[PDB]
Structure formats: structure tokens, C-alpha cells
Amino acid sequence: VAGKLKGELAQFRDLAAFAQFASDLDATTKAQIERGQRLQELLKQPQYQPLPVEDQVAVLYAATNNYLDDVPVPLITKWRDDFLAFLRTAHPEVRKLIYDNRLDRKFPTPEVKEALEAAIKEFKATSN
Amino acid sequence: VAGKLKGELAQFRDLAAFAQFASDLDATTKAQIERGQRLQELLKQPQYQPLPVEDQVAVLYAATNNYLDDVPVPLITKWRDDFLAFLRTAHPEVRKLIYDNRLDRKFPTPEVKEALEAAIKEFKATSNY
Amino acid sequence: PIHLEIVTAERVILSDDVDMISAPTKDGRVGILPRHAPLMTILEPGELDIIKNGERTPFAVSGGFMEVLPHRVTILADTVERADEIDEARAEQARAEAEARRREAQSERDMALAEAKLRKEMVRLRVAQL
Amino acid sequence: PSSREIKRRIRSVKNVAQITRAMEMVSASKMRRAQRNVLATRPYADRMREVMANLTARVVGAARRGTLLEKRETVKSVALLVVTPDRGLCGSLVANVLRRAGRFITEQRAMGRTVDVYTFGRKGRDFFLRTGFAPAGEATRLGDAPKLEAILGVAISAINGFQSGKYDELYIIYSEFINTLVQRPAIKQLLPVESPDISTTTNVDYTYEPGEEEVLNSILPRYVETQIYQAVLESIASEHSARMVAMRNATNNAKDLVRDLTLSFNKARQAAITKEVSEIASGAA
């Protein structure tokens, strides 16, 4: 999952030069910088709040698969916290499934791919 | 001969920051930048290829006067290399004439002047660039 | 013997002394001479004539106005052309206007002007550690 | 502060001064031609200026003072023209004209009249889009020496709306060229009421061959186009002067930064070499 995260974040750092001064960039660059901001803000973890592997994997899967594009940057942290609450209460089984098969060569198993994107859509319908 | 070379190189260095904006500049500024670029390309030299004093004198005389202006910048080095062969083969006498009177107080001279002018004109007419 | 002035929104075409004017007036062509009675009129797409000692230069006027006074005759023609440059076939001015102009006057400037803005912008973040 | 990082800072800022040095003179070169174009266009505007004065004196009847010259009563909707440089780095000129337009808009909305804006240049276009008040007409990518045809795409729409009753008055905001150092925004009426400050020159009468109404209806659209053409051309000259001033200030600021960085680099190297001899002397003993 995190290869796309690292590539997009590095690209966003590259395009920060255009972000600072130029405001005439086309829509693709605007969305590129927006996604970079999404990721870098998502990295704004608070103190004394560790996250297990399944939680971080699910959050990064949601972010990288454009499920978080519509969420504005200031509310992304609250969105993530609510998503963790949703996973801890509504669907602990998807967390258990993700943690169980995190060592597989191809993580995005269709069984893993389902019940997670569906959970993301359910959370999106629930909040905003 | 090289006083004009040094002056033109200094002037081009004064305008070196305008090389990539030479198009939208003064005509004289563009001419100076072009001359400086041609001179720097001329001063480019390969390894283990020494040039005798008379040959350098001829090359600098050709460069200072408006002769290499028609020659494009990327081909200045090849122009010089071919002109050296032309002098070495077509006109062996002009090189000796330059070398013989290199110590004369008046460098330009009338004879050597016409000999070198004729050699340069013949080379530029026979060659295409 | 009347001061003629052909002025256009971009520049002044001609400002010499003229013998006769064959102006294309809206209702019908009129002649204008050294001491003509006062007049100011609309023009129509047509072909104005200027007589220089028996020589006629077709300063075709795409259109505009013309104020005639007993002293001078200014041409307010909004748009005027010339049958010069091989009846505009050579269009030497337009030829340059196509290459010498509209190619290097702004397009060369715009790419260079934008290019400077680039190496300006990128260096500031490269020096954004001071 | 490592005697080498400052060296990179010195090199970078020295580059900035060189770039801005090029920026300062290229705008000045375009400043010269913009002023030259203004002078060339002046006779066209000036010659027809008294023609309005001559024509407005002749026509006095309110009913026949129709079309554009109608001084409409109970003002409802006014369209205003803003002209802005296509690119940035102009300085306070862009802010001043936008602030002037913003003040004018607020004043009219206080009067109860709705407003509209037609923009020249991208800077004005995006500013109003971000404000949320979308301009009805825009004209960007204007050249350094644009022609009258370029502004026809906006002027014709403004006049047609004025004739149709959509707009009852029309204004322009342009960067007035006061001097090479001062470029203040200006507001001008475009409703063709009259221009007799020239005292209608000789105020000589004429025989209107197409007629009073026909001449009036064919000169008013041309008059406002010339006024817009002059204002846009004046803005272009004012833009280059403002950019020239900003670059000259930036170059001096860059040069001041180089000297400030040079002293720090100089102090760091002495501090480094003072250390460099320090331990080796201590190691020797």
C-alpha cells in the first residue's frame, strides 16, 4: 500500500515549489497537490496514540484509493478518528481479517478488498 | 591582435546573464553576445593538439574581423579545424609569412594583411557552413 | 492645399498636404478641396482616393468617419487599407506583421518572460532554507 | 552557518539579483514601446474628442439624445471594466486596482444597484472568480501591444447590454500613468454624455450626410472603444512601470541580502578557521 503513498508525497514535495507561487496550474496539478496535502495531514498523528498495523493499513488503503478526496484537509484527522471508531465498533471483523492475512504476497485479496471498501462506503454514508 | 579579443570577451562576460534572452534585446547587444559565444567556442580546444603561434595569429585575426559571423556557433570549432588544414595545405606560404614577421612592431602590415585576407576569403568561398 | 490627416486607432497613416479628396460618403461620393465647406460624415466600406499632382493612391477605407473643415481634412476612418504591396498581394507590412511581428514581438517575449518566471520561482524554494 | 551553506545562499541570492536585473530592464524596454504606442494612439482619441464636443453641442433634444447617450433615470444595473496585467510581479498596482474596484462595488451595492464586471487579463479574472462574483465577460492573453480587435470581444457585449437596457451605466478601472514611479488606479465614465473640456474646439457645425441619429449611433460605440483601447494601453504602460519599480526594489533588496549574507559567511569562515587552528594547537600540546 505505502509505495503509492511515498511516491505521491515525494511528488507533492516536488510540486510545493509550484504551489507556493504559481496559481495558474491546471486541474491535474491542483488535485495532485490536494492529494499530497491529504497524505501529509493524515501523517499528523497525535501523541500517546499508537495505531496497530491493521488500522494504519486500512487508513492508507482508504486514502490512496481516492476514498478520501472529498474530505477537506482540516477535517481529515477527525474523519480518520471517526473511521477508527467505526472499525472498532461497527466492523471489528474487517480489522481481524486484515491483521490475519497481512503477510500474504498479494494483500489486496478480493476477500480483503471486499468488506473494507464496503466499510469505507458505509462510513462515508454515515458521516457527511 | 588579441586586444580586441580580450575586449570582446570582457563585454560578453558583462552580458553573460543575457545569453538566454538575446532574442528580445538590443541589436548591438545581440551582436556582442553572438560574438562572445563564437569566441568562446573558438577557444575550445581538444587534447594533445598544439597550435603554433602563426596559426593562432591567423585564427585570431579571422575571429576579430567580421568573418566568423556567418559561421554558426556550434560549427566554429570545426570551421577553425578545417581552416587550419586549408592553410597547412592550400596556402603553406601564408603561415611562414606570418611567422617570419611576428616580431614586427606594426602587426597588421600591408602584405601579410592582403595575403591572409585572400586566404580567408578563398577558404570561406570554397567552404559552406 | 488643405492639410490632410489619415489617423487610425493604431497609428497615423499620412499627414501631408492634399489637392483633392474623393471620399466614399454614405449617401454618395463627395469631393473635398483646399477650402471646402464644413463637414463631418460617416464612411462605408469603400475605396477612398487621394490625388497627388495627377497620381491616385487607393487608400481603401474599411470604414470610419471624416471631418472636413475649410482649413484641414482629418480622416477619422476607423479602419483604412492600401492598394500598395502589389495591391496588398505582396502585403510586405502584413508579411512582417506575420513573421517579424506576431511571431517574435510577443510569442518570443511570452516564452522568455514565462521562462524567467520559472527559474525565478524554482530557485526561491531551493533557497527556502535560509 | 557552516561557511558552506551560506556560500550556497550567496550564490542563490546572487542569481536572484541577476534574474531580477534582467527582469528590470526587459519591462523597461516594453515600457518604452508601451509609452510609444500610447503616443501614437493619442491623435486618434484626441481628434475625435472634439468631434464628440462638436456633436454633443449640436444635439440637445432629450428624445433624439437616444441610444448610448441617454442619461437614464432610476439607475439599476451598472457594468464596470477592470483591466489587469496578465502576469504577476507588478507590485501594489494589482492590489490597488482590485481594492479600487472592490470599494466601487461596495459603494454601488449600498446604493441598491446591482453590479457587473468585465475583466482584462487573468489577474482580475481569477480574483473575481475567487470572490464568487463571476465576471460575465473576460479577455485574457492580451499581448504587450494588443489591437483594437482584441477589446471588441468585451466592448461590444457591454454596449449591446447597455442598448438592450441590461446595463444603464458603464465604467472602467485602469491603472492611470502618472509617472514612471507612480501608477494610481483611475475611474472613468463610459456613458457617452459629452467631452467638451476641449471647449468643442472651434465648435464648427456640419451637415450630417447620413443624418443626426445615424452619425450619433455610429460614433458612440466607436468612442467608448477608443476610450477602452486607450485605458487598456495606458494600463499596459503602467504595468511595466510598476514591474520595473518592483524589480528595482527587489534587486536592491537582493543586493542588500548578498552583503548581509557575505558578512555572515565571512564571520563563519573566521570562526571556522579559528577553530581549525584551535584543536590542532591543542592536539599538538
Image (cartoon, coloured by chain):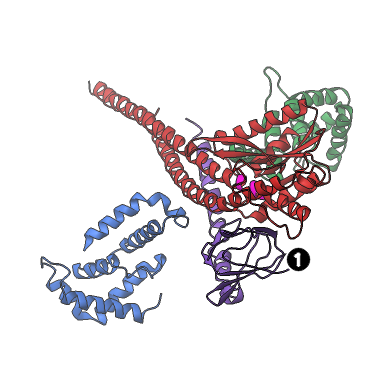
Chain colours: A green, B blue, C purple, D red
**B99 left or right of D239 in image:** left
**A59 left or right of C105 in image:** right
Callout 1 environment at 10 Å: few (<14), some (14 to 19), or many (20+)? few
The amino acid type, in three-letter code, at marker 1 is Asp
Name the quadrant of the N terminus of chain B: bottom left
Instruction: Determine if the magenta segment contains residue D105.
Output: no
Q: Is residue A11 visible?
A: yes
Name the quadrant of the C terminus of chain B: bottom left
The one of D110 and A52 positioned closer to us in this rendering: D110
Residue D2: which quarter of the image?
top left
State the image coordinates of residue D105 (x, y, percent, origin top left). 72, 31
Residue drawn at the location 40% of the way across and 78% of the way down: B128
Q: Which range of residues does the magenta coloring cover? A: D225-231
The one of C39 and B96 positioned closer to us in this rendering: C39
Residue drawn at the location 35% of the way across and 71% of the way down: B79
Residue drawn at the location 41% of the way across and 34% of the way down: D252
Image vertical order of residue D144 relative to residue B106, above or below: above
**Could you tell me which chain the residue with mark 1 belongs to?**
C
State the image coordinates of residue D277 (x, y, percent, origin top left). 26, 26
State the image coordinates of residue A31 (x, y, percent, origin top left). 71, 41
**Secondary structure mostly taken by the magenta-highlighted segment of the chain:** helix
The one of A24 and A57 positioned closer to us in this rendering: A24
The one of D134 and D31 positioned closer to us in this rendering: D31
The residue singled out by tag 1 in the image is C27
Residue B118: which quarter of the image?
bottom left
State the image coordinates of residue A71 (x, y, percent, origin top left). 78, 31
Number of numbered discs visible in the structure rendering: 1
